[PDB]
Image (cartoon, coloured by chain):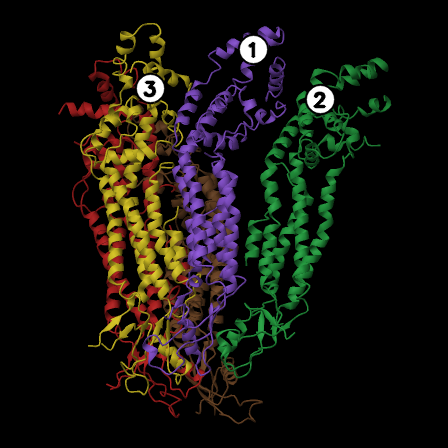
Chain colours: A red, B yellow, C brown, D purple, E green
Amino acid sequence: SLAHTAAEYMLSDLKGLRLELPLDRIVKFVAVGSPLLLMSLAFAQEFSSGSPISCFSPSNFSIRQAAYVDSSCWDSLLHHKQDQDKMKSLWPHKALPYSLLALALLMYLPVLLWQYAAVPALSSDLLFIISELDKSYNRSIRLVQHMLKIRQKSSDPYVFWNELEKARKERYFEFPLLERYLACKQRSHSLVATYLLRNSLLLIFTSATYLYLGHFHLDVFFQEEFSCSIKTGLLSDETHVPNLITCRLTSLSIFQIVSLSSVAIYTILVPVIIYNLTRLCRWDKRLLSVYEMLPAFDLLSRKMLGCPINDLNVILLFLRANISELISFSWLSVLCVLKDHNIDTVVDFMTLLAGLEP
Amino acid sequence: SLAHTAAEYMLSDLKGLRLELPLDRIVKFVAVGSPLLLMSLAFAQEFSSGSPISCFSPSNFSIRQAAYVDSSCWDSLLHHKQDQDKMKSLWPHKALPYSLLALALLMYLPVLLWQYAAVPALSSDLLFIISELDKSYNRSIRLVQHMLKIRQKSSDPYVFWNELEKARKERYFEFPLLERYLACKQRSHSLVATYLLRNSLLLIFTSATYLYLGHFHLDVFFQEEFSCSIKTGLLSDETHVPNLITCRLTSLSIFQIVSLSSVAIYTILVPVIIYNLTRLCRWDKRLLSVYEMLPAFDLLSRKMLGCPINDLNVILLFLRANISELISFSWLSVLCVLKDHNIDTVVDFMTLLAGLEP
Amino acid sequence: SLAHTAAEYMLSDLKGLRLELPLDRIVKFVAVGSPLLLMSLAFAQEFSSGSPISCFSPSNFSIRQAAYVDSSCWDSLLHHKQDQDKMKSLWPHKALPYSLLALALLMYLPVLLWQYAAVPALSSDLLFIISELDKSYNRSIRLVQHMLKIRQKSSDPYVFWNELEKARKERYFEFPLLERYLACKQRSHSLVATYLLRNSLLLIFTSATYLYLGHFHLDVFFQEEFSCSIKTGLLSDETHVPNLITCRLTSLSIFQIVSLSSVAIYTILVPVIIYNLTRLCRWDKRLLSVYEMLPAFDLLSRKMLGCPINDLNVILLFLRANISELISFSWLSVLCVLKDHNIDTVVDFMTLLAGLEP
Amino acid sequence: SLAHTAAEYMLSDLKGLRLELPLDRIVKFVAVGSPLLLMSLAFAQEFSSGSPISCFSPSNFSIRQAAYVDSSCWDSLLHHKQDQDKMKSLWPHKALPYSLLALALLMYLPVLLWQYAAVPALSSDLLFIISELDKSYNRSIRLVQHMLKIRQKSSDPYVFWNELEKARKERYFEFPLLERYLACKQRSHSLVATYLLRNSLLLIFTSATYLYLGHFHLDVFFQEEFSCSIKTGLLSDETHVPNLITCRLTSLSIFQIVSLSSVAIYTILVPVIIYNLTRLCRWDKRLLSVYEMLPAFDLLSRKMLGCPINDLNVILLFLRANISELISFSWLSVLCVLKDHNIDTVVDFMTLLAGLEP
Amino acid sequence: SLAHTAAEYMLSDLKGLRLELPLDRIVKFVAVGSPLLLMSLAFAQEFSSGSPISCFSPSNFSIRQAAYVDSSCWDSLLHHKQDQDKMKSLWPHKALPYSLLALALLMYLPVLLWQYAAVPALSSDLLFIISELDKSYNRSIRLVQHMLKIRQKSSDPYVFWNELEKARKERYFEFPLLERYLACKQRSHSLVATYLLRNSLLLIFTSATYLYLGHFHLDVFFQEEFSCSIKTGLLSDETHVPNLITCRLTSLSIFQIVSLSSVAIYTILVPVIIYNLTRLCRWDKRLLSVYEMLPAFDLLSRKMLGCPINDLNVILLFLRANISELISFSWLSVLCVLKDHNIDTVVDFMTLLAGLEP
């Protein structure tokens, strides 16, 4: 089955960045692999359908004539009701695998749009961001060996403030270019549209699937017997039954169960994308108390105003997922005992020098 | 069969930390792989079922007519009893693989929840804790070694009872950051909730499986013959049998054996999760006797009081399984001969000094 | 099926250079793999063909005679209409896989032409050009150190208003090799033809596919029943039906869907080739403002005049995709804060020393 | 067949330690894979059974009726003997694959028990021993090499019986850390119970297999023809033979051969388990003569007294297998010429210094 | 087929030592893989047997009745000859696969026992012997170069006939540990018993195969038609043929060919085993003429006395296959010139100083 090779080629799980949120990956997995899995279950493995149509041909017919009768109606699914002659078609029974494959291909479009429209740019931005944090951290490394015999011998305030205010105007406190980079990036409105459009495509496709299931299905759902005709052409001048009644659709149960599963999976999937969309509608101030004290992280906390829709929200959402890899997976994360005005200041710095890393 | 592929993808066996207990692993393996194995056995390998329904059609029927007979009843499981006209359905026979796959997928949810909502924080805490405790070694053999050298130069109270306080309560012998970190953790109640929910989901899934097996199964269990009807539609105006009796279900034995095995496996597996849950309801004091001597290992034994339902219990339980990789898989493990007040204290030192460590 | 294999060898995704645009890549993917996917869907997997034609032979015929009748009309697919005796053929039904394979093979010609007659000559140019232009960061505030420091040494115009005509404009700063190379490349008109030919081949082949679908298809489209003759040879002297009416094509629906999808995919693909060919018809000056300040990058924006159909256009088109490999993954992409006269050009400068890499 | 996959997954052949004896390994292999091999041979490959039952239906019956007759008795194996109506079941014929799979999975429990309840503790207790034994090597030859500085030019009585006699009491040569450890492990009894349970499980399991083969088999062994009944339900009101006599079991020979092989393999396997049980019941004093002279091995050759049940026996048993890895695969193994009171003590030493390794 | 799987698992082709003689390897290959190859050839691939028995049922019988007749005699092979009622059985036709697999498994036991009972000690001895023998190179050139250098400074008896006793019988030109090791080992008789038993097991298995082929085969060899009985049970009260004559065995020729090949292969194999056995019954003295001149190799050449059945014989037998790895793959192998007492001793020593090892 092509479902397996589809699952292998597409839907398959720089050098270090996490470019996709776990919830987005879960949503993509569930929305893309479900049609392929349903197609694999329906037309392979357990339920060997064989022939999807059976016909009650008269006993006078031979084997090949019965095969002709049952094969000339599968491609001509038409109910010749006696109620004029409203020939109702049951084409979903034949087009179900095509619809499943079309939905599987369609649900992959937002993934490609995200991956190609804006991923080199985001990679460039965050790569540059991480390319100078390491060098500034190295520039901040050469303070502990300065704070070992100059800091120790003192009457507490002076050196543990005195050398700090000496280091305050000293050029390893004010960061080189971030003060302008963040101003450039926050105001630019280019990358939020990609996120919004990616979520809107999934919502629109779910709505389209609902419309498809509500309009074409739900009508031929409890219909299992239909009467066809063979003498509708060159065979009209022949002596046999003019209405080959009681042609039964063998795989009706598979049809119903596939429809129900397709409805249910997207029904439970709907609110997750809405939550992801609403994630960007607010300014996240969970850990902002500890951010305003650190030199570099003060700038991230400062530019938190105005409309909550700009590139800064997405960049911060991606950095928070990338703030714990190997180097910021440190004191910053360990600074959880500082979440509970002259004592708090000296308590906060003692904790900082307690984790003196080397 | 897709059971093999499902076993390949899901249920397939930082950088050194153990993020799962062996009992939890065996529980997950047994609860996940069992439905897949049952599905593989039931509809593949040994017993090639062929057609799960056989029909005793009258000899006047043709081959294609008999095929239509036996295909028009496998999707219309209905016992047309003469007792009015209660058509009892036998749909579990058709839906057994569906139920098995659904159970296998449902039982994978707690593993995903544990992986997504608790693994990173617990890994971070374990990393910080191990990085702090590995430095506790060169603080009781390298810092305390000047108790044996001074003991032989003096006698009793001012050499062994009056120096254990000015050295134990010394700056190099304190870990205040670790004490504060565990003090803030013992108040937390987030990560224990993940464990409780992970076990509770398995409990409710086992209960739901019990209701499913007790309500739908156990009724169609000893019934192997049912009389169907064909003239319930456009075939009503025809001359043949109106009640085509004795349609026999071929794979009843597989059904019964699968149901019995599913009952037995989970009946055996039930108390294990209960024991896992009650593991957290007590404070474990199996080795505190040797722990309270060490500098850093005194703290984790000190903050051991009050209600046991908290984060520190979980982190310590995971730490016990994580205390023996390559570094603490040493003297700490060898500290078994000191498990049996001023006699052994001078003799427990000589065993400790006997090891020249590197 | 051969479609899977052809997808494995053909269409499978120096040492760092990107010689193909992503739009070109996706165009090639969706132009080459689409007929292979259609062929795989049409004659394998979900829809099991069996026999592509059914015959209504008289009941007197045996099984082997009916098989002969069925097999003697597929290779002689021929409508003997009574309307003299215009013997219309329905050969597209038989020739669809051959046509699909021919189109799939024909789609590869522009790709191989570009890979053979364009890649090495252009790759030499890219390697050489990136090689000179790398020598621009050594001609930075390392060599322009006495320009920011001369602000207080010297005064006003001959600092950062007229200092550039003698101190900057001198032999060390300028590059004669670029001046010699770019003019000759501008006058050259060799490689400007390969891109146009490769796009025009795809356009011509699309038009040919349209003509094929409009002439041979769209006529035998709703025809599913035709009458044949078997007494057109050595069987003429036999007593049986002289014309065997109602030979039904079982796979008419697959034919219709294949034709419709083939039309739709190429209709969607048509404008992208036009966009790609028109990409070269204009000069891109999006980031020319920041290019003319830099020493080496000034020459790229200086030779920007005349007719756009030149080698330089393709060179810069491929360079902008490779301007972010690992070393130019830096300040030039960083300099977004410079896209908003005395304060303007100075602010151009301390932004350069902020990203001083080491 | 699932037997192949079961063989790959289970029963598939620190970092250098040998935690398993070869005899126990071969016992596990021949006890686990044997039922899997029998299952693979019995229901696949050479003997393509097809249908396990053949029925002599009357010639009036059609093909479908005969198929129903032969399929309605395989799942209802019940001998309707005329001797009241003691309908006897021949259910082992249908349950043989289930029994084989149950035994194959069932034999694997002791392996898991040994791997989970004894591997870590034994690995640690043996690793400490080998680590001490490879860290206390230099004090066996080079220790007396400095005493050999005088030995070359000093009289034997006072440089072989008195000068290095004090070196025996010296600080450098003594291993109390073993001396207490051996006794402490000797007083324990935790790990011997795991070995005893592992072997007793195999013994009980073989006896259970014997009970199964003696009670339910050995009765339907020469029976190949049984007479069934079809009119035992809704078909009672029909005109045909009341008993479909002479239903012959096709695969009786496979049944008999499988039973005989299962009996013979375990009959051959029985004494090895007993020998492994009694291996622990005695002191192994094969090489105690050379152990009592060596520094570290004197302690190993000191403590063998009292009851034979202790963890020390298992530890030394596993150490003997690992005493020839790469470093103890040395002079100790070379010391085979010292297995044949003033000349014995001197010949034993010039042999020791003859193999002075570097 | 299991033949391929067995070939992959069993019979599949320290760290440098060669512990199996090429002749032993080819003997094992041609003795183990031959039955597997015969089984793979005969019961698969080219000769698709299908049904191994054909029945000439009367034309009145139906298809299912004929299938019953032909399936109830394959498992009941009994010739109801009219000559009382000597029902001769033809069970080898059914048991040939089982016999072939049993022979294939039986021929592997000596390999396993040799692997498990002789490899460790032999490898230890070989490693010891090589690690001592490789030191002999700097023991005849680095130590005896002052034999021809002094020779030119004097004349005859005190320069080439009186110094050969002072220099040869010196401390550094002696190997006491090695000579004692060989003295101890030539008394041993453990490893030689393994070789003798390994060869005798193949001999007895060959004789058993001959007995099996001569007792059960060679009787049913030209018999292809046997008359069975079907009214030997519940069918006795029926109206049909009491003697269903002419049940023809389809696979007689392949049976004959398999038997002939099995006889011929082992007939060819027999003398190789006896030659391998007789290899140990003599002292090999081919290159021993020069072995008496090297210092260390003199001990290997000295102890050729008494009965040749010793562990020493086997240790040199495995040594000669291992004298040409990389280091003794040298001057020793170069020494072909000196295969054609003062004259020869003085002329021959001109090579090592000329052919320097430095």
Mark seen at residue E139? 2
Name the amino acid type tagged 2: Arg
Mark seen at residue B199? none
Q: Chain of mark 1?
A: D
Q: Is residue D13 visible?
A: no
Q: Quadrant of residue A330?
A: top left
Instruction: Assign a secondary structure to mark 3.
Output: helix
Foreground: A268 or D131?
Answer: D131
Q: Chain of mark 2?
A: E
Residue under label 3, please give it: B139
Coordinates of residue D306 in the picture (x, y in percent) = 44, 26
Foreground: E289 or A130?
Answer: E289
Q: Is residue E224 visible?
A: yes
Coordinates of residue D284 in the picture (x, y in percent) = 52, 29
Q: Chain of mark 3?
A: B
* Vertical comparison of C177 with A101: above or below: above
Q: CA distance from mark 3 to mark 2?
A: 54 Å
Is residue A303 left or right of D137 when viewed as pictured? Answer: left
Instruction: Assign a secondary structure to mark 1.
Output: helix
Name the amino acid type tagged 1: Met
Q: Quadrant of the N terminus of chain E?
A: bottom right
Residue under label 1, please give it: D147
Is residue D329 left or right of D65 when viewed as pictured? Answer: right
